[PDB]
Image 1 (cartoon, rainbow, N blue to C red):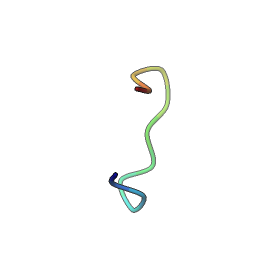
Image 2 (tube, rainbow, N blue to C red):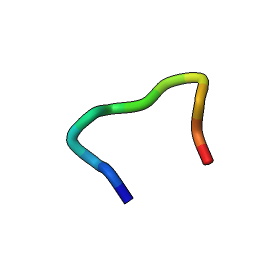
Image 3 (cartoon, rainbow, N blue to C red):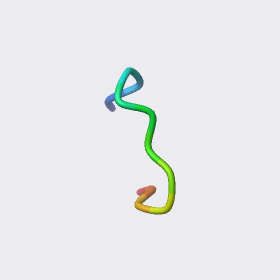
Length: 12
């Protein structure tokens, strides 16, 4: 899973 975009609220 993407780990460079740095998500916040939208976390799956």
